[PDB]
Each structure stands twice: as C-alpha cells, then as structure tokens.
Image (tube, grey):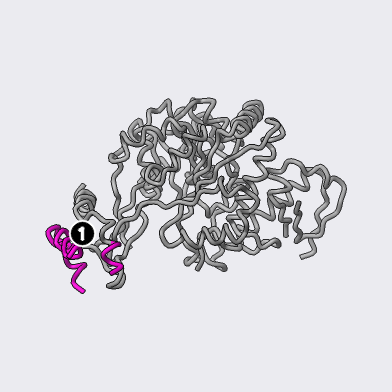
Amino acid sequence: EEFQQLRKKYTDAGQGHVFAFSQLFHQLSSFDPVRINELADKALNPPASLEPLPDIATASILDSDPKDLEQWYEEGLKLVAGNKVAVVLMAGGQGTRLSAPKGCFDIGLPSHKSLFQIQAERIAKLQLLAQRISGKEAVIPWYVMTSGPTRKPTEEFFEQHKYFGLNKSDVIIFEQGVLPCISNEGKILMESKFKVAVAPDGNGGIYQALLTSGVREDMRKRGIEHIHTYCVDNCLVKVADPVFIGFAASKQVDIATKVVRKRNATESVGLILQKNGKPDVVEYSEIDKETAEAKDPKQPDVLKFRAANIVNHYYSFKFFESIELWAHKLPHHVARKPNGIKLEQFVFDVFPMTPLEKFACIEVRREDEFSPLKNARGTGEDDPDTSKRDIMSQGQRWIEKAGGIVITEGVGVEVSPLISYGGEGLEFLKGREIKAPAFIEK
C-alpha cells in the first residue's frame, strides 16, 4: 500500500533491487534514492603550487614570544568565563579496531578512567579555572557527535557515570548524517536483507549536522562565540584550550587549526598549507621529495613545510551562521572499503573557501597535546600503551617541574584533570616523594 509507493520510487531511480527480498520501510523512507544517485554520480565522475601559510597567520608554542602565549591563555580563559566557548566532540568511531564506543576505552591508566571521563574532567577543571576570574559558574557546552551505532551506548554510558560531574543540560549527544553504502556502479548495498548497509557521511558531515540537530541554534541561544572541535581518540587533547581560543579570536578568524611539528622530511603526515593560494590540508602523497625536504630559509634547523595536521580546529560562531551558503559546495569523496564505496565529506574542504586573512594556524607541543588512540595493543604505535605512556610521562613532568620527587623502580604518574588541567596547581606536591606508577586524584 504505502509500502509499494516506496518500492516504486526506489525502482524508478534504479534502486528497486533493495526491495527484492517492515524495518526496511522506515530505513528507506529516510533516504532520497535520487539524492544518492546524485552524489554517487558527481563522486564517480569529477602541478599544484604549494607554499607555507603566511607568517602573519602562524604562531608556535615552541617558538612564539612567551609574552603572546601568556596573553592568549588569559584571553581564552576570559572567553570561557563569559560562557562564550563550546566544544563539538567528533565521537563517531567504535572500539572494534582496538566493542564499545571509542571514548569508553580504558587505555589502562591506574585510575582506569575512559577517554570520555578524562575529557569531561578537563572540561570540569577548566570551568573551575574560569570561575576564579568570573566569580561564577562557567559553562562549556559539550556537543558529542556520535554515529548511529554509538548513540545509545554513549547516552547509557554517560548516564551510568552521572555525566562525570557536569550538568546533564551541558552534555548534548547528537547524530551526524548518514548515507547508504553503494556498489561500484552506485547501487545501494544490503548489510542484511532486513536493513541497509549505511555509514556516517565523513567528518565533513559536521557542518550540516550542526543545523539538523539544532546544535547551532542551541549555541545561538547560549551566546556561543567560539567552538573547539577534535576527535575523541586524542587522549591528550587540551579540551577547549584557552591558548588556542585566545590566539584565534585575537586574529578574528573564521577558522584556525592546531598542528605539531614535522621534524623529519619522510614522516607521512598531512600538512596545513597554502595550496594554490588557499588554505588547505595536503596529504603526504601529494608532497614532492624536494618540497618535503626543503628547509626553512629563516630557520634551517626546521623543515619549510612542517605543520602536521592533527584534526584540531577552531571556528567562529559567525562562520557557523554561514553554513547554509556553502554546505552544498562540499564534495562527497569516495572511500574504497574492494567491494564498495563510502561517500564522505571532508572537514577541511571548506578551508580553501576561507579567505586567507580569516584563517590561522598554531603549532603546539606533541608530547603535551596529541597522543592518538588508533591501534590494538602490541602494535607499538598509536596504541593504548603509547597513549598510557604519553599521559603518565606528562604527569611526571608536571610534578617534577613543581618540585615533586618521583621514584621509579620498574614509568610515570597519572595526574587527574581535576587536580591539574595543564600542569598548574601542583605546588602542593613540592618536596614530597611519589612511587611510580602512581595516581594523583582530587
């Protein structure tokens, strides 16, 4: 009846094969088969000039003036105190490459805290450091962007931990768009017959997702003016980092990015770059050996092209307000996964559309800021062990810097975010001994 109305519209569009054979009816009613055809069509039928970003657009935790760094931290913490700052978490992944949602993974710290909890606590701590200047509660909304599979386990998990101390009203879980799977000839793939194989539409899907879910409208009501985005797998992420916030808003950019230093020319890292006079992210493959090896004229101890992308972004709210102008302009790329294709928009494809003066980039310290969880244990790289080690190494550093004496007879100290957000506030440990492995907690 109504069912056959659907089977007609899909068959007319060359996708009647998915009705070949009751939940299907509903899954398929959420898809425009024609729009699938459009994206499959444009995606299946589509010597660049590379230069570093302008020095006017770049800063460095390592190299910039301690005077500017301190001031940016202060201004960024001002913005947090005025409830102007928001975080959008990219939390789509599952832990299958390592089960549960990725943010639930326990990399094996002494506390056994998940990634979600570690991040929540950095938010809690940061609002508390902001309160010391505002005099009142500070609120950083945490918009958690999940995939379809992860939405309910994420909700139940945050519910089971009582939202890690934050107000339920300040943790907003929501969903990014999805697309069916499609074969090599653009025909929708069938996971089983009772359900379409689907997938999330790339980290570029965030922009449209901010509208559909009502997240942008919620930010508007709150007076949000600055937004930090990152991926849940960065176990060291400085959530809502004031130095980043302060930097970007002092230059009043639409978009800013965080990088770490590429130190050896052969590292396979994406680079934030001027590609054809536009800001862009360039894969390592499109980088020539000469340009990869090029040393900086004004600094031969470092490489010319050294801004290694870590998917860690800043946006103005004004920029979000403009999404309706260009959101359609964003191509759905092809992700081959030898049977099929995944149409994925790319978060950075909007970069070249940004005027150069509206774009900025800050290099940060790897060991304090980027330890990605990507691989199973024993891999030796981007795994729970390197993640564990980076956090416990940072913890020992912070302590030792404030005068603590850490003793290792077998390494590192887990410092809870609630005690210290970024190494501050540890003078109480001056003089005392600590037997590593150890765990410092509120």
Frontmost residue, 50 versus 66:
66
- The image quadrant that residue 354 belongs to is top left
Residue type, label 1: Gly
Is residue 25 inside the magenta stretch? yes
Q: Farthest residue in the bottom direction?
A: 21
Percent of width and height locating residue 66: 66, 29
In the rendered image, which residue does mark 1 sit on? 186
Query: What number of labels is visible?
Result: 1
Frontmost residue, 377 versus 266:
377
Q: Is residue 212 positioned above or below 194 on the image? A: above
Q: Is residue 268 positioned above or below 362 on the image? A: below
* Residue at 19%, 61% in the rendered image: 6
Residue 101 is left or right of residue 389, and the answer is left
* Residue at 36%, 44% in the rendered image: 208
Is residue 73 inside the magenta stretch? no
Q: Residues within 10 Å of mark 1 (few under 14, many from 20)?
A: many
- The image quadrant that residue 67 belongs to is top right
Q: Which residues are magenta?
A: 1-27
Judged by its main secondary structure, the magenta piece is: helix
